[PDB]
Amino acid sequence: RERTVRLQYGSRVEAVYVLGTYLWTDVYSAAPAGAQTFSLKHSEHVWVEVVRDGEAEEVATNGKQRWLLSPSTTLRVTMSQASTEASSDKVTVNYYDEEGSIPIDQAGLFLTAIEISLDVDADRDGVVEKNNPKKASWTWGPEGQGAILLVNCDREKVYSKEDLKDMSQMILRTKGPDRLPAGYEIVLYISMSDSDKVGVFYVENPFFGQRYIHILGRRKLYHVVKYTGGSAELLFFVEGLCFPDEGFSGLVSIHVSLLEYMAQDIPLTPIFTDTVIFRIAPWIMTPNILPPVSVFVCCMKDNYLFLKEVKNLVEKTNCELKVCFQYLNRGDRWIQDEIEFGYIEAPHKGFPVVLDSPRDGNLVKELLGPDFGYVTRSVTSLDSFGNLEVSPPVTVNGKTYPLGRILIGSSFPLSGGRRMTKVVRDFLKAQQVQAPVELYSDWLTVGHVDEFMSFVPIPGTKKFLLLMASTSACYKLFREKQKDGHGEAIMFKGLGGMSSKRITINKILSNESLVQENLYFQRCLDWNRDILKKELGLTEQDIIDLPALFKMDEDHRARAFFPNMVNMIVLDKDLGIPKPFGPQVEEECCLEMHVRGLLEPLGLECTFIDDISAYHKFLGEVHCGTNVRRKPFTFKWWHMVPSRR
Amino acid sequence: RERTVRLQYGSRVEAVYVLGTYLWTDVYSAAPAGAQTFSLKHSEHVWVEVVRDGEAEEVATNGKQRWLLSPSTTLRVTMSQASTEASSDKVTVNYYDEEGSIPIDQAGLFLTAIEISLDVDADRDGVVEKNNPKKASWTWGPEGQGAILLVNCDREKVYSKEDLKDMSQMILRTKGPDRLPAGYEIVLYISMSDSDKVGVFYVENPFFGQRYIHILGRRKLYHVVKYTGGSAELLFFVEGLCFPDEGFSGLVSIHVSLLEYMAQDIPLTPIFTDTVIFRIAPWIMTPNILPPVSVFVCCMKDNYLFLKEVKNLVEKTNCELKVCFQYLNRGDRWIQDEIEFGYIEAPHKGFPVVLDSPRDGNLVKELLGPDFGYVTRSVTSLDSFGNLEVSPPVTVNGKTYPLGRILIGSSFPLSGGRRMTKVVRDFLKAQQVQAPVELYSDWLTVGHVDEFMSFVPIPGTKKFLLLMASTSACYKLFREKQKDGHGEAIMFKGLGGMSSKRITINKILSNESLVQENLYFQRCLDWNRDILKKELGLTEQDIIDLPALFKMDEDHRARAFFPNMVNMIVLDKDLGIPKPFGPQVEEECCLEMHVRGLLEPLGLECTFIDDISAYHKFLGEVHCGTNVRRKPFTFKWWHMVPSRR
Ligand SMILES: [Ca+2]
Ligand SMILES: [Ca+2]
Ligand SMILES: [Ca+2]
Ligand SMILES: [Ca+2]
């Protein structure tokens, strides 16, 4: 970093020198007319080279050497240490005419050397290293570098060092004498565009106590920073205001400049500028294979079997159970549909962050606990978080997705069908590290991917399975039981509001239109199976089909005939599975027995959970919801190398 | 690419098979209840494997082999050649119960195999290869791949193959029997977002002649494509509608799908989809080192010396001269300020493309010739193309910029000064391949980088120089001439409207405020010198300083005292340099002689061009403009690897 400083014809030049740079100095312009040669002297801590046509020669502090004056003969000036009060740092040039050895004039350069570095933790260990030479760039991957910012997820003032504890540190390190020379100041600044992406806090007046003031952000694009002599550090705390999105990459920049005062009405000159970049950490979703921490449940207060059975399930684990009831502004599934658990992470810190999309809007929301960051937002059913899932880590065609891939239900491109809102799809895409895939959920009345699919770990391995609803599996099973003489076996036993229908296996198998409707739904399921296999790199060995059955509405879309078992609580080996209420054979539900026969040999332990008995019947709607909060991946997101956007 | 096709319990399944895929087939669901084992037969061109728990075994066309029925025992079906009218492609499965060897039922799969591939020239040689396996991705670099589109720069109808000659080809290649089976169609489509980025043309009815119809673009997101039997190719022509910009990466996608008809009011199912991506080629600027083709000039019709001298200059070269006059809607420099020559290139074709920003707006604009593509657009003087330059190819800190870097004049970030409009800055940035740098032009009244800087090739080498205006150089020269006894030497000789001012070297050197104003301007120049050296990787050996002098206005901004020599016509070794009208010493302009002494030893040939005499004086404004159209770089832009955006 070479900087231009010219000796002034007929005056001394005084300049601040910033360590890490060096000066090239024109001595030729300040030479009086008619002068021929020049010599120079300089102080102990200034290094001076004479550079003639690109060839550099170090010069002593007081020599008598002379050089011909010439536009192509210049000085190179460097200093390796900042000035103190004991410093007189200078270079003096004397000029000579053709005749005689006594100087006819002299021009000089008086220097004050200071160290200025805006430092961040670019090497991502949680401590702010000195002047990381890569701090002005942000690169992905294990060898990648540059500092990370967390969004402030907790929804002109004064803050202590406690309130800012979760933000990122940025330190302005300086070294120099008691004061900057006359006409200089130091200024921290950001662009107008970044002003809604970040905020920066600082103690403006530490003699009055440490009261952190917001100095950069909305409406404040610059802040003059007071210079302290000697070795000094100013500590700033930095927060992100928003996640990456359509139009925002996640990258922001903060600058510090030493500015020189020219004159009134003249802008100040940026003598030196140092830049750090941050990337705001993306919101990341947790798949079913990650260790469960807490199980969240919502239901009506009187659904007693559901609560007892969920509690019994969780007691088999080390998880905590959190019970929530219904609310005026929210659907009956809201803990599943309106709330999504995810996390954010920086080298120094991370925490869980909940996305909230209340049906009727927000009316206070925690009630979820202080441990969570919280982010709240013409909508269709496809906008629900029931329509959002994420796969376990996969590798596809040699490309690794170490954080898994987000799955979103949609309709065929030319179908004119429903689609999750663009703003939410754009958000998920912009987080980049989960590389989302759209599935086809629009053949379902409600239109949620969690109605037809889920993932479970295979106990005692690092592998997993895709679970798919299958109508073909159900028809096969019922046809077998009928052939076995079980055709009169009744479903919905114990649901009094279903009894008059007297639904048996025979009655189901003889309903011709229902058969055709379910062949079609199987085609819809299989279309998904194929996308999942392609985009997750799965084979048929990775998939288990659970029996399901649907009825068709007037839009030709599906709703559950009996509860969808695939939407289940996965806590490692233990699975809470919705109780299907299937046909009773030998006083056991043939659906429950079939599912156990598929899952148990893999060491998966099945517990059927009754969420419908309290309602006396089942019309395709479930009035309860569950959500599991999980430990984040061990893999650090910033070690991923995502495809070029 | 594995696709799910199930045998149907109690019916035959007919399916289209697309080459490049294969089917996995469930035979277990179609088995009657109570059946134990199955066998199979198949035709000559269908390959069938029995896959038991992931282990695959090829099966003969007619064997007697039997396998136990089981959900985990499936078929894998592949075909390597498309069907003809002579084909009967089929797989038949027979089912058996426990007792007896005669089949109790049979299910079968009748196949029609077709080839479908949407092909583009992804390997960038100008010919459309068959099914490039990378055609759905776009990667930069010499080993990079994916197809390139040109914007249509020539500003519900019918077109011949002639009008579309400059667009990109895309070919849908198919192979199959006389017709698709009942209930299938083929559809080309694009997203709504891409609908303003592209257009696609096709002959809908070739029996009526080849009349190309616009089938995809604004308002048309899909087009049903007629299937022809046998080996067939449908030829599409594709055009880009716009350059990359803020919010548009340059990437677009086109899809073709085989859709299956389900039933009325049911959306059609996308059985197979093939995708090609295009990148729209960026607009690229030509630096002064590229070979000149044509020189464009504008002036008033009576500036005779300018025209004669420019003509004489161009006659020393092989370039063409194009003379343009003044227009009601345009400034006097418009060929320089409102017009910018650049080019676009695709593997098959490229041409020059002019950016047009008329002062008062457009009132027909060519008049520049048919050989050029043409693109026309609260503005300040910084928005002028006089404020836009591009460097020769450089390497900086090991990073190559094989196309050079675009340079744009601006003001200091905190200055509240003028800045080129965001839309234009965003455009230049989005082209990506010239990686623009902002300089400081706002200390100039007009505020154009071309007032203070330019580039010239060094004859007989591959190197170049940066030319910088220097007030220090001028003061040095005048002080020498004064010391030499030339203080009364007069400037502006022959300009009658300057005579009464009687400006001499003495009069200039004694004006104290003008000295201080020009020291300041030199600081502005040097601030630029430093940015240029940093961002272009230049040393002091790459720079020559030309003497310049400015006067200051009420805003503290600079205008030329005498014509700025740095803004010059560079045609290889020959430089048209504005005639400065400097002080006469020994009947030669000391400015002209000084400039010759700097440039000539490098083999640069200097010609001074008088653009001001026709006006009788010089107030800082130039009434003529020039622009040089050049050959594009030999380096292909798509071979560059730009930084992640
Ligand atoms: Ca660190
Ligand atoms: Ca969810
Ligand atoms: Ca090709
Ligand atoms: Ca220009």
Image: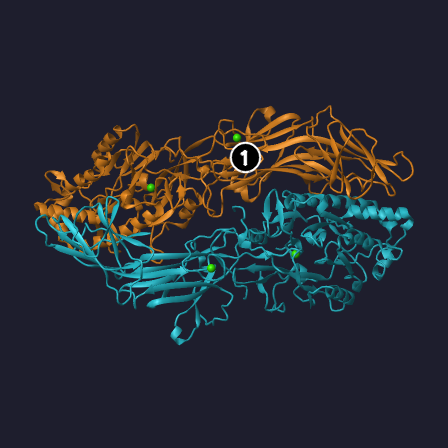
Chain colours: A orange, B cyan
How many dots with numbers? Answer: 1
Name the residue rendered at 54%, 42% in the picture: A194
Q: Nearer the viewer, residue A486 or A341?
A: A486
Residue drawn 44% across the image and 70% down it: B212
Mark 1 is surrounded, within 10 Å at the Cα level, by few (under 14), some (14 to 19) or many (20 or more) other residues, namely many
- Would you say A211 lies left or right of B489 here? left
Residue B311 sits in quarter: bottom right
A123 lies above or below A389: above
Where does residue A14 sit, x and y in percent of width and height?
75, 34
Residue lying farthest to the bottom in this orientation: B208
> Under tag 1, what secondary structure?
strand
Q: Amino acid at mark 1?
A: Val
Q: Nearer the viewer, residue A372 or B549?
A: B549
For the point 69% across and 26% down, the residue is A178
Compared with A608, B566 (above or below) is below
The residue that label 1 is drawn on is A200
From the top left corner, tell me how far across and down residue B644 is, in percent: 52, 46
Does ligand 1 reach within 8 Å of label 1's beta carbon? no
Q: Which chain letter goes with mark 1?
A: A
Q: Is residue A500 visible?
A: no
Looking at the figure, which quarter contains the N terminus of chain A?
top right
Foreground pick, A400 / A147: A400
Q: Can you give x and y, in whole percent of width and height, for residue A472 in the image? A: 20, 49
B236 left or right, relative to B502: left
The answer to whether one can see residue A316 in this image is: yes
Residue B505, percent across and down?
A: 86, 50
Decide which of A257, A114 is in the foreground and name it: A114
Q: Residue at x 91, y 49 (%)?
A: B485
